Image (cartoon, helix red, strand yellow):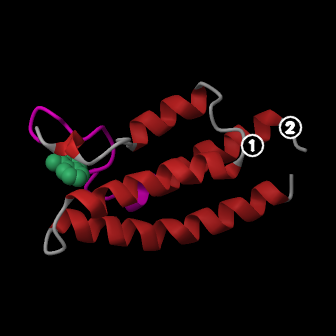
């Protein structure tokens, strides 16, 4: 029970804060299938921050869970695909940790709406 425009402004700010935590920009764009040919073998729904931005602007995120679930896919896909001893796996752990605090604060703000 809130107005659409302030909520989308909040999601835009939140997405920018999450992208800031991905300092290597390894999640900024879809995983390039041309360089990872086996990626889709067990990754059923790829996700990335650019796709999240397009979903946001297409009005596909109307509650915080819609938005947070796609963020969680970025993390979980990366933990699934990559071995634990890789920078990519550890980057997803770091993003989960640093991004979780960003998400908790942003969800508090949405609940004031
Ligand atoms: O090759 C990649 C490039 C950027 C991100 C990736 C996330 N998981 C597996 C592979 C990736």
Magenta residues, dominant SS class:
loop
Which residue does the numbered mark 2 point to in the structure image? 3
Which residue is rendered at x = 13% and y = 75% of the image? 85
Considering every residue shown, the one lying at the far top of the view is 58
Which residue is rendered at x = 71% and y = 60% of the image? 107
In the picture, which quadrant includes the N terminus? top right
Q: Where residue 81 sits in the image (x, y, percent)? A: 22, 57
Q: Quadrant of residue 46?
A: top left
Which residue does the numbered mark 1 point to in the structure image? 7
Is the residue under label 2 in contact with that under label 1 (CB below 8 Å)?
yes
Q: Is residue 80 above or below residue 16?
A: below
Mark 1 residue crowding within 10 angstroms, few (<14) / some (14–19) / many (20+): some
Q: Where residue 75 sits in the image (x, y, percent)? A: 38, 59
The residue stretch that appears in magenta = 19-36
Q: Quadrant of residue 24?
A: bottom left
Considering every residue shown, the one lying at the far right of the view is 1
Q: Where residue 61 sits in the image (x, y, percent)? A: 64, 38
SS for tag 2? loop
Q: Nearer the viewer, residue 19 or 36?
A: 36
* Ligand 1 contact, mark 1 (Cβ < 8 Å): no
Q: Is residue 45 left or right of residue 87?
A: right
Estimate the spatial distance between the alpha carbons at disc 1 and disc 2, rounded to whole Å: 7 Å
SS for tag 1? helix
Which residue is rendered at x = 77% and y = 34% of the image? 5
Is residue 48 within the magenta segment?
A: no
Q: Is residue 18 above or below residue 61?
A: below
Mark 2 residue crowding within 10 angstroms, few (<14) / some (14–19) / many (20+): few
Q: Is residue 63 left or right of residue 41?
A: right
């Amino acid at each position: 029970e809130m107005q659409l425009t302030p909520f989308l402004i909040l999601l835009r700010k939140t997405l920018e804060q999450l992208q800031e935590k991905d300092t290597g920009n390894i999640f900024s764009e879809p995983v390039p299938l041309s360089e990872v040919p086996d990626y889709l073998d067990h990754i059923k729904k790829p996700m990335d921050f650019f796709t999240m931005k397009q979903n946001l602007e297409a009005y596909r995120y109307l509650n915080f869970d819609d938005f947070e679930e796609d963020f969680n896919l970025i993390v979980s896909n990366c933990l699934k695909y990559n071995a634990k001893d890789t920078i990519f796996y550890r980057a997803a752990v770091r993003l989960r940790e640093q991004g979780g605090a960003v998400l908790r604060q942003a969800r508090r703000q949405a609940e004031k709406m």
